[PDB]
Amino acid sequence: MNDLMLDKSALLFGVSKYLEKGIITGNVLIHKSLLAELERESNDGLVSAEIALDEVKKLKDITERILVNFEIVGDDSKKGEANELSREYCLEKGCIIVTADETQKKICDAMGIQYNFLQPLKQGLSFESFFDDETMSLHIKEDTVPRAKKGKPGNWKFVNLSDKPMLSTDVRMIANEIINAVRLIKGSFVEIERRGSLIIQLGNYRVVITRPPLSDGWEITITRPVVRKRLEDYNLDERLIKRLEERAEGIIIAGAPGMGATTFAQALAEYYMRLGKIVKTIESPRDMHLPPEITQYSKNYAEIGELHDILLLSRPDYTVYDEMRNDEDFKLYVDLRLAGVGMVGVVHATSPIDAIHRFVNRVDIGTIPNILDTIIFIN
Amino acid sequence: MNDLMLDKSALLFGVSKYLEKGIITGNVLIHKSLLAELERESNDGLVSAEIALDEVKKLKDITERILVNFEIVGDDSKKGEANELSREYCLEKGCIIVTADETQKKICDAMGIQYNFLQPLKQGLSFESFFDDETMSLHIKEDTVPRAKKGKPGNWKFVNLSDKPMLSTDVRMIANEIINAVRLIKGSFVEIERRGSLIIQLGNYRVVITRPPLSDGWEITITRPVVRKRLEDYNLDERLIKRLEERAEGIIIAGAPGMGATTFAQALAEYYMRLGKIVKTIESPRDMHLPPEITQYSKNYAEIGELHDILLLSRPDYTVYDEMRNDEDFKLYVDLRLAGVGMVGVVHATSPIDAIHRFVNRVDIGTIPNILDTIIFINSGNVSKVYTLEMTVKVPAGLKEADLARPVVEIKDLATGNTEYEIYVFGEQTMIVPV
């Protein structure tokens, strides 16, 4: 009964499901213009366009068995944007726009065009099924069975979630599902997109996507952080807690790799926030699990001197510098300390004294205690 | 009895053949627009356009043979994309679209335009006939006879497969055949296209295509992966296998060139995967033969710091760094190790001090065993020697007493327990070699 005009967003969302399931009803209309767009995009090698186009057929298929029309319209003088043309069509013919795009929704509302706004089923995401409350990361690759890392950082096992390999089409669908979710989820954004790789923050999930030719096949890795070890869980000496609370300003946390030095720092940073201190972190890449009250900078995306300047205006109480390696890292730590900023630096060294050598050359000996006052060793 | 409208995809798919065979039948139509496009492309030097245009004549000739019409249609006045115009023409006049392009198929299906979708005539590809069970690679060049590399990776022999040279036209046709196959074959993609070169992954085949002016003639080299040697096929020492399974985190596989160091690393990576470890590889270019459970990154196409971030975010258990040559390579290895990622590094060297020399300058002495713990030497496809690294607090020499206290790294033979070399610092840091 209703005439429905579908935009690209509807096709990239899975509108075919809604149709069959009866959530929406009527004839299906797609503007010629949109098909033209999809064609070019498909030719330009856009992955989304394959998905969108594939959706067109399903729609036609369902249209066939439920005794409803399916048509493509508007080729005469078809000079413009698909969304704009499709609206115009709906205005002149009284059709209904179906979309998953808020922007389109808003314009339709203004123009007085009837519209149907698609809403994710409350079930959050495809891949969410595989996630366990105890699953650390999910690994998906072309021609591969999905696999998961289950446990805690100390104790975990590796697992196969299925015996069926994952098809290439399916992987790309999941990647698309994830890109769509950025708009929908809170505190989600694309970190960086490169020709071979895409890195995403999706709620608490961290997503890394790789594609040929960088990788041999499409791969998606989704990770979720484990429960943060609190400072209290480290059963701490009263002498030390007092020091941290009241006297310590230039700190180094040292330990051999895998001995828990980073994790401790994370715990200390959270503790200091809870004490009412302003805390910030510098990491590369950003991986610590901390609340939003603590701002986490990823140095990789920072321009030269950018962090230095931001931190000197911000003047936080403590800055946690994770995995200090480069001369620039040590220089920045010293600069901040000289500026009166508290620091917690993570140096992976096997002996605490070894943590110092890199600091010792940078400053005059009389200034050294002002740079560093406390070194905490982790085993 | 039908009117057939051919798109570019059909012209690149040897549609002339189909017509002869009667697989498709009717009059042939080509839209003006498409011919205009082929012309411009041909002038811009597109190789495909030459092929596509050549196919037009073939079509015309065949039409004459089978007594069917051939025509070029559409007003010169109308402008647009050839595919869009061709579809429009079909709608108005009831013609049938002939194509090998899935996109066009999908759009035609939607628009309710009848179409004929071309499917490859033979399952195998042209060149696949030339491959035998024991052939490693196939070499094709203008004015040369086809040739192949056959036998053992250590003991391969070159051969001629034919009497007659291949004309340039034949080589370009094969290249095109291969480009077309990317769409069809599973797990295929264009690695990279440059002005003079094209590199392709086609199923398990690797294809390299070169053309002038980069090369003196058109050349196509097609290679197939070798049978992979399993870790078990090396009948390794029990002491060693235990180490690899339960204690070795920072590994370097070393040897002389051609002695099998890379192949051993490939084997070890496979082994670890089977143990349920997550394994990834860094190589340049990507050549190892590994199952899809192991992901292989080609470093050449990676941006600065890209791999470092990916690997730290998606945490694998072991990363295999093949042919470590650059300072950046060693840095990354160290970064990953510090982050607790296991490494298998391939360094072609004859001496342990030579293999490890590049690592020693990077970190404080106490931290060295944490970067590197095990060094495996490969010779003639087997393990020559294994060294282990540990840090001790000791005066290097009890008689010398030059420094009363010292912390040192001892490099010990796995078999003898014999500290063949020591590492410590006394002004600039030096390696020793005890008798």
Image (spheres, coloured by chain):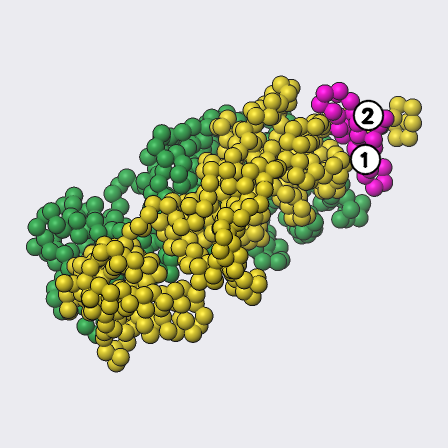
Chain colours: A green, B yellow
Is B338 placed above or below A314 here?
above
Q: Label 1 is placed on what type of residue?
A: Met
- Residue at the outermost bottom position: B77
- Measure how far apart labels 1 and 2 are at the Cα level: 15 Å
Q: Is residue B47 above or below residue A116?
A: below
Residue B94: numbered disc: none
Which chain is indicated by disc 1? Answer: B
Q: Residues at marks 1 and 2, common chain?
A: yes
- Whole-percent x, y for residue B144 in the image: 53, 57
Q: For the stretch drawn in magenta, what is the main secondary structure?
A: strand
* Foreground residue among B156 and B324: B156
Q: Which class describes the residues within 10 Å of circle 1: few (<14), some (14-19), or many (20+)?
A: some
**Quadrant occupied by the C terminus of chain B:** top right
Q: Mark 2 belongs to which amino acid?
A: Lys
The residue identified by callout 1 is: B431
**Subunit of mark 2?**
B
Magenta residues (range): B408-435
The residue carrying pointer 2 sits among few (fewer than 14), some (14 to 19) or many (20 or more) residues within 10 Å by Cα, namely some
Q: Secondary structure at mark 2?
A: loop
Q: Which residue is mark 2?
A: B394
Quarter of the image for residue A376 reads: top right
**Looking at the picture, does residue A273 appear above or below residue B77?**
above
Seen at 49% across and 43% down, the residue is B224
Q: Residue at x 23, y 70 (%)?
A: B70
For marks 1 and 2, the one nearer the N-term is 2
Q: Nearer the viewer, residue B262 or A51?
A: B262
Counting from the top left corner in percent of width and height, residue B232 is at 56, 24
Q: Is B192 colored magenta in this rendering? A: no
SS of the residue at dot 1?
Answer: strand
- Locate residue B279 relative to residue A11 in the image: left or right: right
Residue B130, image x and y in percent? Answer: 45, 46
